[PDB]
Image (cartoon, coloured by chain):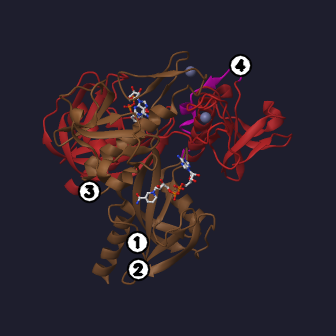
Chain colours: A brown, B red
C-alpha cells in the first residue's frame, strides 16, 4: 500500500482514471517515466506491479482518449487485471466521498484501500460483486442464448449476480431456473475472472442438463437453444471466461463424440 | 422483492434486525404469528421462504435479546442462511441512508434489493466480500494453524479476503504465501458458503503442497504445522466451512492411503 506524490524517478504502467474510464493515448495503456505524461507532482496510488514495473493509479481525467479498459484486454492477463484494479479503485473512492451511514465526508485510509468516516465509526472497502457463469451441456449440445439487455447477435452462456445469503451453487440453480426453466446437475467449478464492468468477480461453472423444457424470461433472454458442438452460432470473444467455458464444452464433446 | 405492512395473521420466521444483530428471545429465532411479536402494522420485507412459511425482515431493535446470528447456526443451513440474509440486508439499507456520491438521501428500489439516488443516477447493491479458505494437503498431512486473532486452542485452515482485481486462485496462493510462506499447486474448488460476519462469501479450496517451509507472521498466526490426517488436533465445530474442508481433506487422504 503506497499513496504518494509522483517524482521524476517514478515509472511504469499508468492507469489514469475517472468515472469508469481510463486514459488510453494511442489506444495504449500509458508506459514509461512520469515526466513523460506530465504526472510529476501528481498524487497517485501504487496498485501493484507487473514484471518489475509498478502499476499506478492517478485519479484525474484527461481531455482526450478516455475510454473503456476493455480496449486493452489483449494485454497480459495479469496486467489487464491490474488496470481493472485501477478503474475499480477510482470508482470506489468516487463512490464513497460521503458516508452512507451519517452523510458526513469521508477520508482515505493509509493502512489499506478503504474509506473511513470522520464523524462516525464506519468503514467501506471496495465492492466486488460475485457472479456465476455456467455453460450447460446436453449430450452433444450446449445451451446458448441471446441477451435482451444488450443486443449483439452473439449467443453465449448463462450468467448472473450471486444474491445475499446464497451459495454459488444456489446462484447457478436460481439463475438458470429463472432464465431458462431447466434444471442442471453435476456442477463443476472451472475458474474465476475479475470483470471490471463495473465490479464483478466471475465464477465459471460447467453443468449438465437434468430436466425441464426451455422457457425463457424475455426480460433477460431473446431466445435460447441447444446447439450441437459442431454447428455453433456467434460466440463471445476469446479472452472472456464465457468463450472458454463454451470451448471446454465443445472440445469435450468432440473428444467424446 | 416484496415489501408490506404486516397484518394480524402474518406468520413464519421473523428476522428483527438492527446493527449486525437480530432479536433472539430466549436465544432462539422468533417463529409464529405477527400479533405474538407485536409486529402488526410494521413494514416488513419477505427475504425468503422456508418450508412454505415466509421468512420476514423487520428493521427495528428490541430492548432485550439482540444477539449475533451465529446463535442460530446450529439450526439448519437454510434458516441460518436466511437469518444471515436478513441481518446483512438490514446493514446494507442502514449503510446507504445517504449517497456516497452526492450526499443526498437515497431511496430503496421497489423491484430489487438496492439503494437508489434521485439526485445523480448512481446506486448501490448489497456488498458481498469474497473470501478464500483453503485446506493445504501434503501427502498424508494437512496444514493446520492457530490464530492470534482469536486464541481458543483450535487448529483450523487458512482464509483471507479476495482483493480487487485478483482471481480466487491468486487469492489462495497469496494468503497462503503471506501467512505460512509456502507455495501451493493443484487447487480444487470444493464449495461455497455465505458467512454473515459481517458479510462474506467463503470459497472453499483444497491445495497440494508444492514447496517452501513454514514461516509465519505472528500478526496472523500463533503457530502452524503439518498434521497427519488420522491424528488431528481440535477442529472447528461441525457446521462451519472450515470443518467441512478438513473432513473432506481427511476423507481424501483416506481414499488415497488406505
Ligand atoms: N465472459 C465474461 O467475463 C462475462 C460474461 C458475461 C457476463 N459478465 C458480467 O457478469 C455480469 C452479469 O451480467 P448480466 O447478464 O446479469 O447483465 P447485467 O450486466 O446487465 O446485470 C444484470 C442485472 O443484475 C443487477 N445487478 C447489478 N449489480 C448487481 C449486484 N451487485 N448484485 C445484485 N444484482 C446486481 C442489475 O439490475 C443488472 O441489471 C455483468 O457484469 C457482465 O458484465 C462477464
Ligand atoms: N469456518 C468458517 O466459515 C470461517 C473460518 C475462518 C474464517 N472465516 C471468515 O472469513 C472472513 C475473512 O477472513 P479473516 O479471518 O482474515 O477476517 P479478518 O476480519 O479477521 O481479517 C481481515 C482483515 O481485512 C479487513 N477487511 C474487512 N472486510 C474487507 C473487505 N471486504 N475487503 C478487504 N479487506 C477487508 C478486516 O478489517 C480485517 O482487518 C471472516 O469474516 C471470517 O469470519 C470463516
Ligand atoms: Zn459516517
Ligand atoms: Zn447521489
The region drawn magenta spans B62-77
Q: Are marks 4 and 2 in contact (CB under 8 Å)?
A: no
Q: Which one is closest to the eye, mark 2 or mark 3?
A: 2
With respect to residue A225, does B232 lie above or below? above
Q: Which one is closest to the eye, mark 4 or mark 1?
A: 1
Q: How far apart, in angstroms, are the residues tagged by discs 4 and 2? A: 62 Å
Farthest residue, direction front: A63
Residue B128 visible here = yes
With respect to residue A23, does A254 lie above or below? below
Left or right? Give the position of B165 relative to B28. left
Q: Are marks 1 and 2 in contact (CB under 8 Å)?
A: yes
Q: Chain of mark 1?
A: A
Question: Is the CB atom of the residue marked by disc 1 within 8 angstroms of ligand 1's nearest atom?
Answer: no
Q: Specify few, some or many for label 2: CA neighbours under 10 Å numbering under 14, 14-19, or 20 or more.
A: some
x, y (%) of residue A208?
A: 44, 71
The label number, if any, that marks residue B63 in the structure image: 4
Q: How far apart, in angstroms, are the residues tagged by discs 2 and 3? A: 41 Å
Left or right? Give the position of A33 relative to A132. left
Question: Which residue is label 2 attached to?
Answer: A232
Farthest residue, direction left: B212
Q: Chain of mark 4?
A: B
Question: Which residue is label 3 attached to?
Answer: B255
Instruction: Mark 1 vs mark 2: tell me if same chain.
Output: yes
Q: Are marks 4 and 1 in contact (CB under 8 Å)?
A: no
Question: Which residue is label 1 attached to?
Answer: A235
Q: Circle 2 — which element?
A: loop
Amino acid at each position: 500500500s503506497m499513496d504518494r506524490i509522483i517524482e521524476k524517478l517514478d515509472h511504469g504502467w499508468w492507469v489514469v482514471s475517472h468515472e469508469q474510464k481510463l486514459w488510453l493515448p494511442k489506444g495504449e495503456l500509458p508506459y514509461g517515466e512520469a515526466a513523460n505524461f506530465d504526472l510529476v507532482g501528481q498524487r497517485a496510488l501504487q496498485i501493484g506491479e507487473w514484471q518489475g514495473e509498478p502499476v499506478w493509479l492517478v485519479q484525474q481525467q484527461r481531455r482526450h482518449d478516455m475510454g473503456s479498459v476493455r480496449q486493452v484486454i489483449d494485454l497480459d492477463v495479469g496486467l489487464f487485471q491490474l488496470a481493472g484494479r485501477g478503474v475499480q479503485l477510482a470508482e470506489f473512492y468516487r463512490s464513497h466521498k460521503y458516508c452512507g451511514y451519517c452523510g458526513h465526508e469521508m477520508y482515505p485510509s493509509k493502512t489499506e484501500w478503504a474509506m473511513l468516516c470522520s464523524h462516525c465509526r464506519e468503514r467501506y472497502y471496495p465492492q466486488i460483486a460475485p457472479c456465476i457463469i455456467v455453460a450447460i451441456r446436453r449430450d452433444d449440445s450446449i445451451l446458448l442464448a441471446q441477451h435482451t439487455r444488450h443486443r449483439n447477435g452473439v449467443h453465449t452462456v448463462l450468467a448472473g449476480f450471486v444474491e445475499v445469503g446464497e451459495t454459488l451453487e444456489q446462484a447457478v440453480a436460481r439463475e438458470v431456473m429463472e432464465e431458462s426453466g431447466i434444471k442442471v446437475k453435476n456442477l463443476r467449478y472451472v475458474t474465476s475472472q475479475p470483470w471490471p464492468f463495473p465490479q464483478s468477480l466471475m465464477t465459471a461453472f460447467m453443468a449438465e442438463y437434468d430436466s425441464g423444457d426451455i422457457v425463457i424470461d424475455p426480460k433477460e433472454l431473446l431466445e435460447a437453444n441447444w446447439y450441437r458442438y459442431d454447428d455453433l452460432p456467434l460466440l463471445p470473444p476469446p479472452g472472456t471466461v464465457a468463450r472458454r467455458l463454451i470451448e471446454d464444452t465443445v472440445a469435450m464433446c468432440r473428444a467424446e463424440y
